[PDB]
Image (spheres, coloured by chain):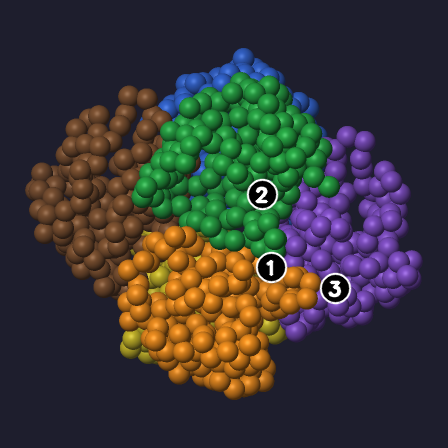
Chain colours: A purple, B orange, C yellow, D green, E brown, F blue
Amino acid sequence: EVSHDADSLCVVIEISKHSNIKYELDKESGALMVDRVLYGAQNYPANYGFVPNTLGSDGDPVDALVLSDVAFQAGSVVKARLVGVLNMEDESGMDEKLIALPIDKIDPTHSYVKDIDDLSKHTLDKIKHFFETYKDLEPNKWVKVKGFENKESAIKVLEKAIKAYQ
Amino acid sequence: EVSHDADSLCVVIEISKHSNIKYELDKESGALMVDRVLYGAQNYPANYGFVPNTLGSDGDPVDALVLSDVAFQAGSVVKARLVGVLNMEDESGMDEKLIALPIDKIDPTHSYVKDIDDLSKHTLDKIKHFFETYKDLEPNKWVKVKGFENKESAIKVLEKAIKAYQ
Amino acid sequence: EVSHDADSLCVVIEISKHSNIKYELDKESGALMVDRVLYGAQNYPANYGFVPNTLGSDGDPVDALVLSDVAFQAGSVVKARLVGVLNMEDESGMDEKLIALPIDKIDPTHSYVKDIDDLSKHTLDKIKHFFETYKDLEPNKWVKVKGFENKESAIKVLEKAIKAYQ
Amino acid sequence: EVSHDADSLCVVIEISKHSNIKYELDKESGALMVDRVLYGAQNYPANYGFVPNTLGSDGDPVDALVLSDVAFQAGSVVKARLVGVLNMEDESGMDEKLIALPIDKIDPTHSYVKDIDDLSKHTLDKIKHFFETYKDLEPNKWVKVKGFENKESAIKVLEKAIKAYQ
Amino acid sequence: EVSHDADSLCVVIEISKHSNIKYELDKESGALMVDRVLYGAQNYPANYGFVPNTLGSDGDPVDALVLSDVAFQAGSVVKARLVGVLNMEDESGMDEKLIALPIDKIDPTHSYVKDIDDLSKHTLDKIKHFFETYKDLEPNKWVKVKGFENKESAIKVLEKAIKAYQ
Amino acid sequence: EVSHDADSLCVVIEISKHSNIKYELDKESGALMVDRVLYGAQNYPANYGFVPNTLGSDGDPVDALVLSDVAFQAGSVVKARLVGVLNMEDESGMDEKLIALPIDKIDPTHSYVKDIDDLSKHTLDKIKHFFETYKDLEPNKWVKVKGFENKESAIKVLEKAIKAYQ
């Protein structure tokens, strides 16, 4: 039962916070595939996944970062709420990463975060710097981060991705 | 192949020992859902899960704690054996938590534990205190632990849950 | 070179965040003594230590919690800044726990926290609940938490402890 | 989509590197079963799994060790490449363990390893010693390791296992 | 203040439970030296250290294993109580390893263990097997474990070591 | 007893491999000070420390990276052997980082590495990229990595640092 509610959307976790291993769920066998081990001495600054039944810019489900103090197991599903979006350009084109938090029912730790600007400057910079450099060592690949936009913008991105899938 | 044998019953793990993240398996997609992150500075004193094809007091499969020195991955299934049951009352009514150990074929570490009284006083108190306080910070929720009962009592609870499902 | 500056005071770490092992530094050999392993399924919600050359209510150096996203090694020393104080009563009398953060030069993650009220409600409740229950299982011991006071109050506590030592 | 290419074969991970818990995937429910907790103070020297749609010496899919600096989650699937095979005899008969590495696209860390002899003497000895002793404490079970053979030999083992399944 | 009381003797921890890194304290600088990284895929089955101001069979302070569910930091000191001794022969001669537990004041988890026979068969076998094989891969070194003796025997070993130092 | 032998020099560890916390030993109290928590989502690619009784380019003891598969505890001392040196320029001037491995007596895992060129291209690139970016987020600070030089060059750096201290 995939929920597309901006304040309670399902996010399938593929990368656990702090891990340097990117997994990728196969949409036909449900197999969690080992996709990449970071080339650099880095670790994902947040849990990372995708929103089912959506179609993002690159033809794959729209991506979402789920910020939390804890790391969720790759393969699990967490109900989250949008607070913003991170825009970036890579060798394939534009890419968007929804910025979310688990719903308060799951973990109210950051219930005070209502919009992108409520997140600390330090956290935003860390996330931006990660995407800006995590593919440095990968040949023929690169990422140029543009910046973050608020929840209103993120909702537009989500709805556009939902409509595209339909 | 779900086994309901008291000395070798299947337990689907939803919470790994030492974790502060409670997962919950969805019975229709097999999706491991992130259900709750403990509000307090606590961690589950044992692996936690449910017995398939059973119907407990609250309408959900009967719960079981699988005591072990190691933490089993959420989503895995372990064959266990009963040694007792923990009775408690929450805001919804009575609740029972079967107390089990992996079968000796899997891990014989605590093969000497034949009944609830074989478990140390310290371990029992730690488990009781966990359930007695882990929901303190959650509004409108609470737990009043009654105490532990032996294997004979646990078997009755299991059989009643098995019959109810049938 | 022990600094007693409220915005840059030295804190000797004795307990690492997330650990259930309390160490205690011996002031004569510099030996890090294993003092206690929590009886319950809990873990320290922050790094914990004391301020050298001070004399608190119980005759020992004044205690300080150093809030951080990371865990500092027991035995290390971190320069911190005060943001508040936690008052509680135990079986021995009143006790105070200074609430601090590493100085921005060390980690600016929570540089936005200027006073106790800047900390999230969730974090404060978790800390309070920890002290309120972590000694439940210890016989003849108990803790009744009163509440938190601001940085202005914490500074008074520190200065009083510094003067007492002198 | 199971790939049987020697330089890109699918390996279903059942044991994560450094873990002392052996899981076993059930081929009918996809359930990850807890199979064994090592009796000794040991840990798997590599990620461990099997190659789907193959039939090894003991009637089960052929086993493969996936050497890596990182530990892959039990239940995930990694595309690997063969570099050798480890031959051993146990109480049931001969057994073979394919020796592999993730494909360079996933992690190029050990891209320099082209054949068994490229692996360090220390790593080979550690792996051999693990299988030679990890079942010492298990009654009625034992392992006598013969030695390692090169990639050419491993390919023969794989093809024979693939044909047997067909 | 080194205590030589059999029921409360000081043990300086040099190896943390589960670690594969053996440290060794230098008695002149207090420097914790990295001494050895296990050659095999193994990990210490208990915390390991020595009793200050004693002289064991090999001319060094008498060794002690401190059994616990938790791992103590290398370099820390824990007050323990004897429950037995493990006798073994290596390439240098006879060696004895005192078997201890933290005093109940520190952690009462295993307060029920009064003598060697109170420890589980599984734990004893795991410890014995560790010493029997952890030096297999080290050239010119080996260990032949004899067996465990009770607390009465351990006390004799300790007193003899204390007298020798004096 | 500080050894300055190129093939067995003492290295005081201040940063443990994989950690994002940089400690710094105080040369007057032996206090392990918390110096910095990385601003980015990164982790040290190796154990890091300094060689006692030496004087490097910046007036502090010469730095050394100790490559290993395991992480050594901050504050410990490991005997290492040189295999190269990493040259870089920061906002303060030129800086050199000796590249070393534990001596074979401690851990022979990488005994095959005799000179810088024996290290994998992947490991060298990861280390270089770490220093090139780990200070990106720190204001008024930066690092421009030049490249690695062999053991012969590293020895010159060490001897020059030893003479300078004398």
Residue E151, image x, y percentages: 14, 52
Tags 3 and 2 on a common chain: no
Which residue is more in the foreground, F48 or D16?
D16
Chain bearing tag 3 is: A
Residue under the image location 85 percent in, 38 percent down: A91
Q: Secondary structure at mark 3?
A: strand
- Identified at 33% across, 78% down, the residue is C91
Can you say which quadrant of the picture contains the N terminus of chain A? bottom right
Relative height, residue A107 to residue C49 (above, below): below
Q: Which image quadrant is residue C136 in?
A: bottom left
Alpha carbons under labels 3 and 2: distance apart:
27 Å
Assess whether mark 1 and mark 2 are in contact (beta carbons under 8 angstroms): no
- Crowding at dot 3, Cα within 10 Å, few <14 / some 14-19 / many 20+, comes out as many
Q: Residue at x 55, y 70 (%)?
A: B53
Q: Which of labels 3 and 2 is toward the front?
A: 2
Quarter of the figure with residue A61: bottom right
Q: In this view of the protein, can residue A64 be seen by the observer?
A: yes
Which labelled disc corresponds to residue D13? 2
- Counting other residues with Cα less than 10 Å from the Cα at mark 1, is it few (<14), some (14-19), or many (20 or more)? some
Q: Which sits in the foreground, F8 or B8?
A: B8
Residue at 67%, 48% (x, y): give it: A32
- Percent x, y of residue C144: 42, 80
Position of E70 compared to C126: left or right?
A: left
Mark 1 or mark 3: which is in front? 3
- Secondary structure type for disc 2: strand
Labels 2 and 1 share a subunit: no
Q: Amino acid at mark 2?
A: Ile
Chain at tag 1:
A
Residue at mark 1: A70
Instruction: Please name the residue that numbered disc 3 is placed on.
Output: A10
Quadrant of the frame with the C terminus of chain A? bottom right
> Above or below — where is F120 with respect to A52?
above
